[PDB]
Amino acid sequence: IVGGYTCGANTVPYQVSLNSGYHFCGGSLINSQWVVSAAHCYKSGIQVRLGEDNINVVEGNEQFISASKSIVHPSYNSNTLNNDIMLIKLKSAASLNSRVASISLPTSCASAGTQCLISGWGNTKSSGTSYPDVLKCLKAPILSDSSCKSAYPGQITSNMFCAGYLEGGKDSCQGDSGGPVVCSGKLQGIVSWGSGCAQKNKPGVYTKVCNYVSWIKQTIASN
Ligand SMILES: N=C(N)c1ccc(CNC(=O)[C@@H]2Cc3ccc(cc3)NC(=O)CCN3CCN(CCC(=O)Nc4ccc(cc4)C[C@@H](NS(=O)(=O)NC4CCCCC4)C(=O)N2)CC3)cc1
Ligand SMILES: [Ca+2]
């Protein structure tokens, strides 16, 4: 997260860290057994870390649970990043409490102009590399599809939306991938891609979760 602020310990209780010996992507807890992340975050041997604030210090609210399976959307295209969504099943159920909680899936898509909360442990520098200890947060509005396509001509599919600030300075970044964009209490986006981070006229591009709710619910029910 570039240009954000310290969320506060366990204030984003659906935020998880995906760990393969080190933090490499975010995710969002959607029930006690399932995490939503980005397809481009797929790796074997993922350990899901819940209840994290400082990812480098054991603070006493962590749950470390191996992924038992991952289901990458079958239509994911790793060139265009269309359908950049994956579901991770936990080997055992997370224990839900005030610090580890699921986020609701949308019942409708969000509208341009709505403020959303984007969070993660990704890079905080637009011109360099710097990874934080504690979870970082950014408030950012959904941008119009027209301004999104104007920034990224030919590159935006119906399964993507832009959010952030055309002026630059405030954005998600590498290592935030797969984590949440929550708008009006609902998981509306997944950190997916962008041209650089926090650059002028290149807002963040996010997987449009509202297009996938039926797929998510049927997949987690059957698997
Ligand atoms: N809000 C934000 N501004 C924001 C937030 C989060 C991100 C993070 N998400 C990205 O990085 C995604 C997705 C991605 C990630 C990794 C790889 C490829 C893609 N590579 C691997 O895994 C290695 C394994 N293998 C997979 C891919 N194969 C070939 C296919 C391929 O070439 N496809 C591809 C490559 C690049 C892009 C899209 C598709 C665009 C890229 N943008 S960029 O060029 O400007 N670079 C950014 C990266 C973050 C720091 C600032 C510069 C992008 O965004 N990519 C072979 C390799 C970024 C921005
Ligand atoms: Ca910790």
Image (spheres, rainbow, N blue to C red):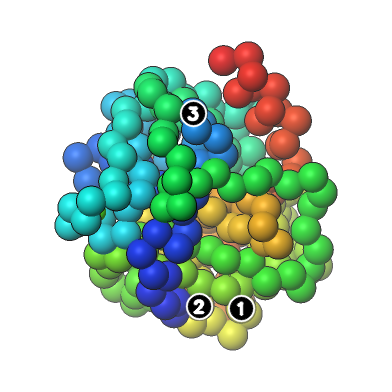
What type is the residue that disc 3 sits on?
A: Gln
Amino acid type for the residue under numbered disc 2:
Lys
The answer to whether the residues at label 1 and label 2 have Cβ atoms under 8 Å apart is: yes
Please give left or right for residue 52 compared with residue 209 in the image.
left
Residue 170 circle label: 2
Q: Earlier in the sequence, mark 3 or mark 2?
A: 3
Secondary-structure class at tag 3: loop
In this picture, is 133 found above or below 95? Answer: below
The residue where tag 1 is placed is 165
| Mark positioned earlier in the residue sequence (1 or 3) | 3
Q: Residue at the location (35% across, 37% down)? A: 48
Q: Quadrant of the N terminus?
A: bottom left
- Per the image, the residue denoted by label 3 is 33
As measured in the structure, the alpha-carbon distance from the residue carrying label 1 to the one carrying label 3 is: 34 Å
Front of the two marks 3 and 2: 3
Label 1 is placed on what type of residue? Tyr
10 Å neighbourhood of mark 1: few (<14), some, or many (≥20)?
many
N-terminal of the two: label 1 or label 2? 1
* Residue 163 visible at all: no
Residue 14: horizontal and vertical position, in percent? 49, 49
Q: Secondary structure at mark 1?
A: loop
Q: In x, y percent, where is residue 2?
A: 42, 74
How many C-alpha atoms fall within 10 Å of the one at disc 3: few (<14), some, or many (≥20)?
some
Q: Residue at the bottom extreme?
A: 167
For label 2, the SS is loop
The image shows residue 107, relative to residue 9, as above or below, that is above
